[PDB]
Amino acid sequence: TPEIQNLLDTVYNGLQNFDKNKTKLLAAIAPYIAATLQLPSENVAHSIL
Amino acid sequence: GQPLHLPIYATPADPKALLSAAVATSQGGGKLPESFISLWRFPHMLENA
């Protein structure tokens, strides 16, 4: 769907310039997941991942 | 002429549930313009930008 594709584009531009050994992948993707799934917290987005 | 039977009672119609559809669109992102080199060194062009 174009909406899930918009999610893909936003996370693609967002987590571009990432290294694995710098920081956790989950904490990096957690804000875009919290926004696109409209979740209030960030620990909830941690939880669901 | 009064009928012995009592008349049947009608059942009212079912109301419609008005429903809206909310969809989103996907506009394509813009690419970069061409690299044009300048005279200036790094800090002056950095402060300018």
Image (cartoon, helix red, strand yellow):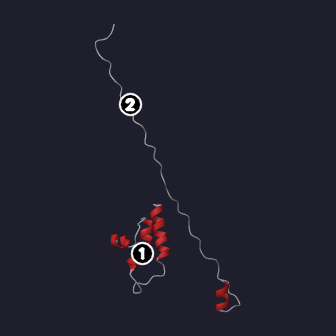
> Residue farthest to the bottom?
B41
Q: Secondary structure at mark 1?
A: helix
Tags 1 and 2 on a common chain: no
Question: Quadrant where the C terminus of chain A lies?
Answer: bottom left
User: Which residue sits at x=36%, y=26%?
Assistant: B10
Q: Chain of mark 1?
A: A
Counting from the top left corner in percent of width and height, residue B31 is at 59, 74
Residue at 48% x, 81% y: name it. Answer: A17
Q: Nearer the viewer, residue A40 or A13?
A: A40
Query: x and y percent of residue B7 in the render?
Result: 32, 18
Q: Position of residue A12 (x, y in %)?
A: 47, 73
- The crowd level at tag 2 (other Cα within 10 Å; few <14, some 14-19, many 20+) is few
| Farthest-out residue, left | B4
**What residue is shown with label 2?**
B12
Which of the numbered marks, if any, corresponds to residue B46?
none
Displayed quadrant of residue B43 = bottom right
Q: Residue at x 49, y 56 (%)?
A: B23
Q: Tag 2, which secondary structure?
A: loop
Q: Residue at x 39, y 79 (%)?
A: A25
Residue on which disc 1 sits: A29
Q: Position of residue B26 (x, y in %)?
A: 53, 63
Image quadrant occupied by the N terminus of chain A: bottom left
Task: Residue type at mark 1: give it.
Answer: Ile
Instruction: Nearest to the eye among marks 1 and 2: give it.
Output: 2
Q: Nearer the viewer, residue B6 or A6?
A: B6
For the residue pair B26 and A33, the one nearer the viewer reads as A33
> Is B39 drawn above or below residue B1 in the view shown?
below
Q: How many marks?
A: 2
> What's the amino acid at mark 2?
Pro
Disc 1: CA contacts within 10 A as few (<14), some (14-19) or many (>=20): some
